[PDB]
Length: 102
Image 1 (tube, rainbow, N blue to C red):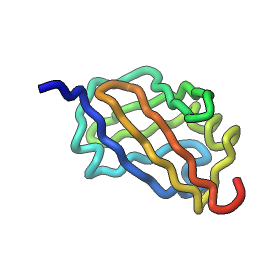
Image 2: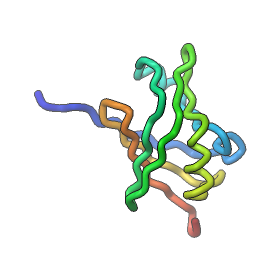
Image 3: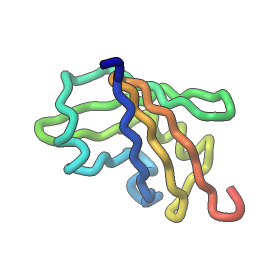
Image 4: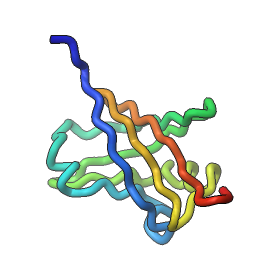
């Protein structure tokens, strides 16, 4: 049985909160308990990567500071949708859906 892990999830973003933090859905969060990481990397299909600071605080998790570099540099707003492909570690692969324009 060779399967490291690949869970994929999509999230609609609210720019109002995505301005400073990436909110991970509680039900999906409950699915993966892990020790608190210092930094997590977000990989982009075009070749860029953003190192974000992510914390699991109690029951919940937020990718806070650093995520703003992603939102601002890649430019996403309410209406954009992201696909997160996870392995089994702190590797997050993100695909960005603009809308019609980025």
